[PDB]
Image (spheres, helix red, strand yellow):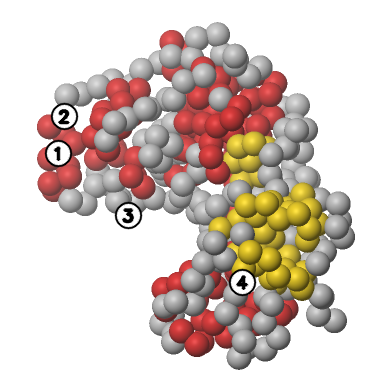
Amino acid sequence: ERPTFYRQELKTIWEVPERYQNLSPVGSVCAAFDTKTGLRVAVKKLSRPFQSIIHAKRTYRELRLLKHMKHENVIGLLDVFTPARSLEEFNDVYLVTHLMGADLNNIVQKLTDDHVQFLIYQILRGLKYIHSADIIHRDLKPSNLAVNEDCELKILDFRWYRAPEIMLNWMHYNQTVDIWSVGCIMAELLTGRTLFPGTDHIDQLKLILRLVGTPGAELLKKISSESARNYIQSLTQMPKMNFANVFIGANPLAVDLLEKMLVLDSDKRITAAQALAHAYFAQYHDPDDEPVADPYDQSFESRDLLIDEWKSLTYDEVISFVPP
């Protein structure tokens, strides 16, 4: 049976099941109390969800993704509703997720090594799942990582932390773009400072290469553009620094892990699954409690449909939603 909804203004009018109380603003988002569960939640009212073909497809994309994610370290979907009673009336979409405490920016007085391990382990646990569904986050950074009091972490959403190959539009990449990002995050947790605080994309790459070294003949062989090759090999040859002397006093196993994540060639970069079995995580790792995802069907991405069809497909997804 359909809940009872009530209506309220806070620019626009919000129409939500009565189980959600004390909406205070934070599309646009309100913090809410979910009376059914006692949880504090975030209710997002999508703005303009079907204004165009692009809006519609993005609406469908976000809803499908959030429905797929079912993992402790990844934001999932608590509820999705519409005030509409039919496809005819369907104009509004609300998403309900866990209201998350801080993010990792708020946390950045250093963190102990034990606590760095705990945070990074959880990110890698979430990333192993996301990547096992063939999804690449692409923009992992402190503001996309929320923690509660217990300091339990969830990945949300989906340029100091971007892999150089994602930064530079290179088609030679894989899911370990996210692993570069984790390396930058982990480093900043150990030292209190941004690893690569570039001013523009050039300054950023110069800071990266200063630490990792200019590409070696082997990586140069994977570069298909002559102007790109000529560009690279014209730069002054930086040799790979030793990380120990950049992360002084850090746990030697953290430093070793950093050297494996912060590798320019992504075919050689450590993966989320490999990183979880690294000794640095010995107190937290458990290979029977690092679950993987169902395969995630992104064929919709290649389709060009009418507005009314993306709208209908979205409505289908609302209707079939099953809560946790």
Q: Can residue 178 be seen in this snapshot?
A: yes
User: In the shown orientation, is residue 66 left or right of residue 193?
Assistant: right
Q: CA distance from mark 2 to mark 1?
A: 7 Å
Whether tag 2 and tag 1 are in contact, CB under 8 A, the answer is: yes
Along the polypeptide, which appears first: circle 2 or circle 3? 3
At label 2, the amino acid type is Leu
Q: Earlier in the sequence, mark 4 or mark 2?
A: 4
Q: Tell which of 187 and 200 is nearer to you.
A: 200
Q: How many marks?
A: 4
Amino acid type of disc 1?
A: Tyr
Where is residue 28? Give x, y as percent.
Answer: 56, 58
Whole-number angstrom distance, CA of label 3 to CA of label 1: 17 Å
Of 69 and 78, the residue lying toward us: 78
Front: mark 4 or 2: 4
Q: Mark 3 highlights which residue?
A: 171
Residue occupied by mark 1: 231
Outermost residue, bottom side: 88
* Amino acid type at image mark 4: Val
Foreground label between 1 and 4: 4
Mark 4, other Cα within 10 Å: few <14 / some 14–19 / many ≥20:
many
Q: Is residue 86 above or below residue 173?
A: below
Q: Is residue 206 left or right of residue 92?
A: left
Quadrant of image for the C terminus: bottom right
Report the residue marked by disc 4.
93
Q: Secondary structure at mark 1?
A: helix
Q: Which residue is mark 2?
A: 235
> Mark 4 vs mark 3: which is more N-terminal?
4
Mark 4, secondary structure of its residue: loop
